[PDB]
Figure 1: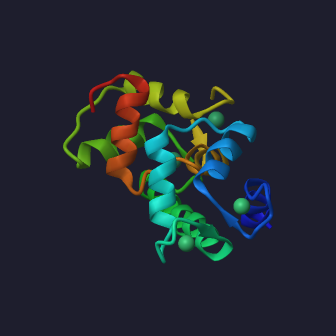
Figure 2 (figure 1 turned 45 degrees about the vertical axis):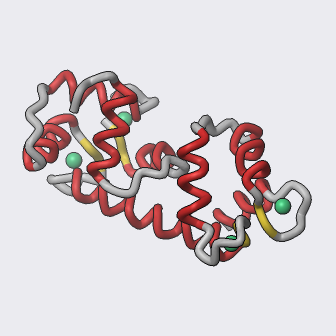
Length: 152
Ligand SMILES: [Ca+2]
Ligand SMILES: [Ca+2]
Ligand SMILES: [Ca+2]
Ligand SMILES: [Ca+2]
């Protein structure tokens, strides 16, 4: 019950839906730091029937689709399929997208994502981008830009 756990956590009054207040205060009470336009981007993406409310199916679907996207990004970065992402792979991937960066810049990115202080694996990746509403590698790169300060 991934998304059941999350939803049950967020739905404070237990009326079966999560409103924007519950999402905000919820994310803060779970310790996930998000800006209002990120949270609102999540909400607008999730509210398929546009009633200003997230029911369980909408929530579950958003997180499912998002997880698929992030998994796709991960597997697109992992060139040698070792289930991990090395800095050189970030360099190559960004190079195919017309960005030339150095090894220490990629290392900087990875360290911004890693906690083990090694390179990042699928668990850290997934956890890091779980509530980050980036939709693809481009948006991930833009996020890396305002996160690390490097202009990429
Ligand atoms: Ca509610
Ligand atoms: Ca809705
Ligand atoms: Ca790899
Ligand atoms: Ca690591």
